[PDB]
Image (cartoon, helix red, strand yellow):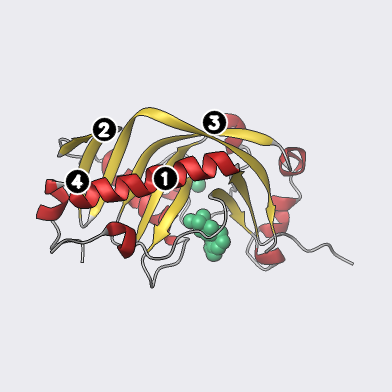
Amino acid sequence: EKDFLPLYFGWFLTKKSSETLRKAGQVFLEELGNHKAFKKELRHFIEKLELVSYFGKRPPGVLHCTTKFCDYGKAAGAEEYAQQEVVKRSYGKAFKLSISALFVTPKTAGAQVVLTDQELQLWPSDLDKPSASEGLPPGSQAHVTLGCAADVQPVQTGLDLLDILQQVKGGSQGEAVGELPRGKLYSLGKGRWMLSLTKKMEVKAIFTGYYG
Ligand SMILES: Nc1ncnc2c1ncn2[C@@H]1O[C@H](CO)[C@@H](O)[C@H]1OP(=O)(O)O
Ligand SMILES: [Cl-]
C-alpha cells in the first residue's frame, strides 16, 4: 500500500525563532496602526483600528514557511514533490531563512522570505500562480504568515505578496512614507503596506512535513 504524504511540507521555525518573529510581527502591527500615514489612508483599507485585532486569525503553532501543500496526497503534484531526492535529503535538516520585509494588506500580514539557491531546490515547480507566470523569479512569494482577516485563507498570503512584489517590480513602491525603527515604511495603495528591513532577519528552521 501507498504511504500517504504530509498535510504540507515546509520550514518550521524553532521555538526561539518563531517567538522572535511573532513578537516582531506584532510590534510592526502596533507601530503601523499608530502611524500617521496609516491612519490617514484608513479609507482604502476597510477612533483607531488595532491591526492585531484586525488580523484575528494567527498561526496557532510555530511559525513556518510552507513549500508544498500536499493534503496527504490529494493536492496536485504532491507525490511528485515528495518523491524528490532533495526533499528526502533535506527532511529533518536545519536551515537559515532570511526575512527581508514585513507586509500587510486588507487580507493578510506576513514576512517575506528570500530563499537561497539551496533552499529554492525545495520550492515546488508546479504552484498555481507561480512567480514565473508574473515575471518574478521562482520562490519570490516565499513567506511566513503572521495573521489573516477572519474570512481569509492562509494561502492568500502568498498571493498578496506576489501582488506586492509585482508592484515593487513596476517601481511603484513610492517614496517611503515613514521611517520605523527597523526600516522604511512604504504605502503601496489599496491598503497594502511594506516595512523594508534595514537588516534582514535571520530565523532558524527545520525542513519537514506536518501531518496534524
Ligand atoms: N493551496 C493551499 N491550500 C491550503 N493551504 C495552503 C495552500 N498553499 C499553501 N498553504 C499553506 O499550508 C498551511 C496549512 O494550510 C498554511 O500555512 C497555508 O498557508 P501559509 O503558507 O500562507 O501559512
Ligand atoms: Cl514560484
Which residue occupies 20% across, 57% down? 190
- Above or below 191: residue 122: above
Picture coordinates of residue 131, whole percent (x, y): 45, 46
Q: According to the image, label 2 marks what residue? A: 181
Q: Nearer the viewer, mark 2 or mark 3?
A: 2
> Which mark is on residue 187?
4
Report crowding for label 1: few under 14, some 14 to 19, many 20 or more residues within 10 A (C-alpha).
few
Compare residues 85 and 46 and report the one nearer the observer: 46
Picture coordinates of residue 120, whole percent (x, y): 57, 37
Precedes in sequence: disc 2 or disc 3? 3
Q: According to the image, label 1 marks what residue? A: 23
Compare residues 133 and 139 and report the one nearer the observer: 139
Precedes in sequence: disc 4 or disc 2? 2
> Which mark is on residue 116?
3
Q: Which of marks 4 and 3 is in front?
A: 4
Cβ atoms under marks 2 and 3 closer than 8 Å: no
Judged left or right of residue 200, residue 31 is: left
